[PDB]
Image (cartoon, coloured by chain):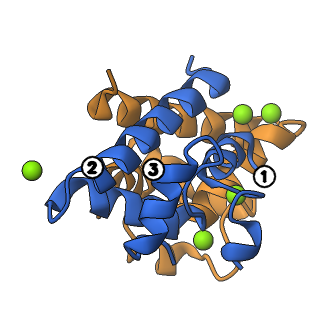
Chain colours: A blue, B orange
Amino acid sequence: FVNKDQIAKDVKQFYDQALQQAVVDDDANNAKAVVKTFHETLDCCGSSTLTALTTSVLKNNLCPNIISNLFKEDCHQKIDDLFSGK
Amino acid sequence: FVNKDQIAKDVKQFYDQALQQAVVDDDANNAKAVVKTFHETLDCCGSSTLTALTTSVLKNNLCPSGSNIISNLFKEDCHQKIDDLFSGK
Ligand SMILES: [Mg+2]
Ligand SMILES: [Mg+2]
Ligand SMILES: [Mg+2]
Ligand SMILES: [Mg+2]
Ligand SMILES: [Mg+2]
């Protein structure tokens, strides 16, 4: 079987690495599109565990309310909710 | 190391497992909730590995309001939407 907690953990890692890659290297095709899609699909922006990357991602219009829940319902929370059925 | 291919495979399997339980187990509140969340979040209904099941999935009200046999035929399946999520499309 696929364990919920493990796949949620793996997806959060995928998102985190993408967030990092999205701000570290700029004017690049991959990382920013992945991030934008996660943000639009899950309705979130950044991660409470990565505030500096979250700031960079806000400054660079990679996020679509969202602000009211910026860290109350961050992308890690939405990923958990996806696999938990919330 | 994060492995995009393997994560996508595991998400698809997770969905398929939940869908299969959702149609056969009446007390599977979690499985039903999982598939309903995937369907709403990814804007899909059913998978390409379980095409024959889509009729029961709909009858079971596991797809978002408006979903019906014909409307769903003009939509990508959940596996493609899962692939799209991890490829940024
Ligand atoms: Mg490149
Ligand atoms: Mg949700
Ligand atoms: Mg269940
Ligand atoms: Mg389940
Ligand atoms: Mg949605």
Q: Amino acid at mark 2?
A: Val
Residue at image point 76% right, 74% down: A68
Does B50 sit left or right of B20 as displayed? left
Q: Which mark is residue B47?
A: 3
Q: Is mark 1 within 8 Å of ligand 2?
A: yes
Q: What residue did someone put label 2 on?
A: A24
Front one among B15 and B3: B3
How far apart are the two marked residues, 1 and 3, measured between alpha carbons? 20 Å
Quadrant of the rendering where the N terminus of chain A is positioned: top right
Tell me the crowding category of disc 3: few under 14, some 14 to 19, or many 20 or more residues within 10 angstroms, Cα based.
many
Q: Amino acid at mark 3?
A: Ser
**Res. A32 in view:** yes
Chain letter for the residue marked with disc 1 in the picture: A
Q: Where does residue B83 sit, x and y in percent of width and height?
A: 33, 50
Does A1 sit left or right of B48 as displayed? right
Q: Amino acid at mark 1?
A: Lys
Residue at image point 61% right, 40% down: A49
Do the residues bearing badges 1 and 2 touch, measured as CB atoms within 8 Å? no
Badge nearest the viewer, 1 or 3: 1
Tell me the crowding category of disc 2: few under 14, some 14 to 19, or many 20 or more residues within 10 angstroms, Cα based.
few
Q: For mark 3, give the secondary structure.
A: loop
Q: For mark 1, give the secondary structure.
A: loop
Q: Which mark is residue A78?
A: none
Answer with mark 1 or mark 2, whichever residue precedes in sequence.
Answer: 2
Q: What residue did someone put label 1 on?
A: A86
How far apart are the two marked residues, 2 and 3, measured between alpha carbons? 36 Å
